[PDB]
């Protein structure tokens, strides 16, 4: 276990102990108050006995009167001392409650403002291919203890308040309790609202009329008996503007930007795991309301209303999903992805709904592109420092081959996916995404195997192959054709020594695969640097299969 995590567990055990201590004190204080009340009635009976001396022999009366006086004077003195003891125990209990609430405040800030935020950030980067955020198991186990400890303390101070109503003692206790109560309502509000979270986000590139899912959960749901009357959670699609004003409490009526089919779900309690979660499995976007379409951000607002405890402590919880870009056609998916990638990667913590920086530094963009690239190609072979130099030369229209020279250069959103690259009809994102699309669709094994060098220009291709045996070739990414793969090969000749074949695209690869095509060209012998062609591609050569129409009753490879 981590050291930061062990300290959290140490504090939970410390908080449990001090809450037991105030429970014991409150039981002692209830006994003192009850005994004091019996003794107060004993003082009224001394008075009643004095009135019963009216019918007594004044010789015997003298004895029974001095005795009643000695009893009254001592019981009166005891009662007065006991009254200050009751006030002192009530102050020492309020001080103890104030002390544990401050330790609980520090503990809750760690759980909610750091550990939960880290998990949410991990879930946010996972949308770009980052490593999975992991189970909410730990955050739930911690939030359960926050709920259990704040509740135990609230019911202790409700019991203390009953005692004060039963026997009021004016003084500093009344304002110490008024303060402890304010601290409790803040802790409970922050805990309830902050633990209503999306476990499984909806798709960030969302086509209308397409089934989609999301999972919301209340981390403290089982501990505060919210599972008793499981609340209905409703999902609505809202705009970036509607989200901004929603958080500033300017929601006019019930603002929304479209309709979600099957947008209602009742939370389900799972006794074994203690989890209270709404699983929306069949949501669908029926319509969307507009104001680029691929730059327009929406969010799925999940809201619910429930109360904590037998009585009415009602909470209205709201949680916004990570921004979503709504497409209708499917061809819009590529540009929508850039808007999502920029948001997921560069959102500053604590931002107002969907504010992103205009510019980032080249190494920040590199981290985002490499994370996306490996998720798309499904490989651990990502963008090397050389590949980054190639993309930096392309993006900045620079000649440097030193990655360090690009360190302090900034890429704006328009430089990434608005303005086209010099002398081209496409943006840097459209070029990079075109490479990912061609690799993902047909060449995942080839990319993983090292068979596609790709991120080299014509001059780099020339200088790598110049001193290689004839038939040495590399597969490169085409500049002129988005999603294109061109063969560069060396073969000594009078005109040129290096040659670039016409690039292939997914349409060509659907008719005949890259491996089948390379296998047909007998003049391609070595895959750069010196790997025999069949060694790298033979695994993927289509074995010619005979057909049923040609008279073959059993499958046959002809
Ligand atoms: C059939 N067979 C046995 C063969 O050997 C035929 C091979 N073949 C050829 O000869 C073809 C036939 C016509 C001339 N051809 C050429 O390739 C000639 N070259 C070129 O035409 C070009 C090279 C490049 C490179 C690029 C780039 F590198 F990608 P970029 O980064 O600037 O974008 C861009 C444009 C061109 S045009 C040449 C001879 C080699 C000079 C072959 C190549 C590709 C295709 C395609 N089919 C489906 C799509 S592309 C079919 C024919």
Image (tube, helix red, strand yellow):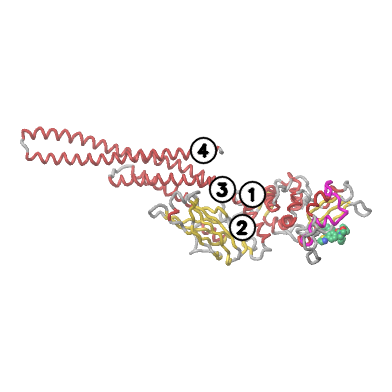
Counting from the top left corner in percent of width and height, residue 425 is at 75, 61
First in residue order: circle 3 vs circle 4: 4
Q: Quadrant of residue 83?
A: top left
Vertical placement of residue 255 versus 275, above or below:
below
First in residue order: circle 3 vs circle 2: 3
- Tell me if label 4 and label 1 are in contact, CB under 8 Å: no
- Report crowding for label 4: few under 14, some 14 to 19, many 20 or more residues within 10 A (C-alpha): few
Counting from the top left corner in percent of width and height, residue 152 is at 40, 45
- Tell me if label 2 and label 4 are in contact, CB under 8 Å: no
Decide if ligand 1 comes within 8 Å of the CB at mark 4.
no
Q: Residue furthest front?
A: 553
**Magenta stretch: includes residue 521:** yes
| Dot label at residue 130 | 1
First in residue order: circle 2 vs circle 4: 4
Vertical placement of residue 292 versus 159, above or below:
below
Q: Which residue is mark 4?
A: 7
Counting from the top left corner in percent of width and height, residue 542 is at 79, 57
Disc 3 from disc 1: Cα separation: 15 Å
Q: Is residue 399 left or right of residue 227?
A: right
Q: Which residue is mark 2?
A: 204
Q: Is residue 183 left or right of residue 85?
A: right
- Report crowding for label 2: few under 14, some 14 to 19, many 20 or more residues within 10 A (C-alpha): many
Q: Which residue is mark 3?
A: 135
> In what element is the residue under mark 2?
loop
First in residue order: circle 4 vs circle 1: 4
Q: Which residues are magenta?
A: 509-532
> In what element is the residue under mark 3?
loop
Residue lying at 8% horizontally and 35% vertically, measured from the top left: 61
First in residue order: circle 1 vs circle 2: 1
Counting from the top left corner in percent of width and height, residue 558 is at 82, 59
In this rendered view, identify the residue nearer to me: 231 or 235: 231
> In what element is the residue under mark 1?
loop
């Amino acid at each position: 276990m981590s050291q930061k995590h062990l300290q959290i567990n140490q504090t939970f055990e410390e908080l449990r102990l001090v809450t037991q201590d105030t429970e014991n004190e409150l039981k002692k204080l209830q006994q003192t108050q009850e005994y004091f009340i019996i003794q107060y009635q004993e003082s009224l009976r001394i008075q009643a006995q004095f009135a019963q001396l009216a019918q007594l022999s004044p010789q015997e009366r003298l004895s029974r009167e001095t005795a009643l006086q000695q009893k009254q004077v001592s019981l009166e003195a005891w009662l007065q001392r006991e009254a200050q003891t009751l006030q002192q125990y009530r102050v020492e209990l309020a001080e103890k409650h104030q002390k544990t609430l401050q330790l609980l405040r520090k503990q809750q800030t760690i759980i909610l403002d750091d550990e939960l935020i880290q998990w949410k950030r991990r879930q946010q980067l996972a949308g770009n291919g980052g490593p999975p955020e992991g189970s909410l198991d730990v955050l739930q186990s911690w939030c359960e203890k926050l709920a259990e400890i704040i509740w135990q303390n609230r019911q202790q101070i409700r019991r203390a308040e009953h005692l004060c109503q039963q026997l009021p003692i004016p003084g500093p206790v009344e304002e110490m309790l008024a303060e402890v109560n304010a601290t409790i309502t803040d802790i409970i509000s922050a805990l309830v609202t902050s633990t209503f979270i999306i476990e499984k986000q909806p798709p960030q590139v969302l086509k209308t009329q397409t089934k989609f899912a999301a999972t919301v959960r209340l981390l403290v749901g089982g501990k505060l008996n919210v599972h008793m009357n499981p609340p209905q959670v409703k999902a609505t699609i809202i705009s970036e503007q509607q989200a901004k004003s929603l958080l500033k409490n300017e929601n006019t009526r019930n603002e929304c930007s479209g309709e979600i089919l099957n947008n209602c779900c009742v939370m389900e309690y799972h006794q074994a795991t203690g989890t209270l979660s709404a699983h929306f499995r069949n949501m669908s976007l029926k319509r969307i309301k507009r104001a680029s379409v691929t730059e327009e951000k929406f969010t799925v607002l999940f809201e619910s209303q429930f109360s904590v405890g037998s009585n009415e402590l009602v909470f209205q919880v709201k949680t916004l999903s990570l921004p979503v870009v709504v497409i209708v056609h499917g061809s819009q998916d590529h540009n929508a992805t850039a808007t999502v990638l920029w948001d997921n990667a560069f959102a500053e913590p604590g931002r107002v709904p969907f504010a992103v920086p205009d510019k980032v530094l080249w190494p920040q963009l590199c981290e985002a592109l490499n994370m996306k690239f490996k998720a798309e190609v499904q490989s651990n072979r990502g963008l090397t420092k050389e590949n980054l130099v190639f993309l930096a030369q392309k993006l900045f229209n620079n000649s440097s081959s030193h990655l360090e020279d690009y360190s302090g250069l900034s890429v704006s959103w328009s430089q990434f996916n608005r303005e086209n690259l010099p002398g081209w009809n496409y943006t840097f994102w459209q070029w990079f995404d075109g490479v990912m699309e061609v690799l993902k669709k047909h060449h995942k094994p080839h990319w993983n195997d090292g068979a596609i060098l790709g991120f080299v220009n014509k001059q780099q291709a020339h200088d790598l192959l110049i001193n290689k045996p004839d038939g040495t070739f590399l597969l490169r990414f085409s500049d002129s054709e988005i999603g294109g793969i061109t063969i560069a090969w060396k073969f000594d000749s009078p005109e040129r020594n290096l040659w670039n074949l016409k690039p292939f695209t997914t349409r060509d690869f659907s008719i005949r695969s890259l491996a089948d095509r390379l296998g047909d060209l007998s003049y391609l012998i070595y895959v750069f640097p010196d790997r025999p062609k069949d060694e790298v591609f033979s695994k993927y050569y289509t074995p010619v299969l005979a057909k049923a129409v040609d008279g073959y009753v059993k499958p046959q490879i002809k």
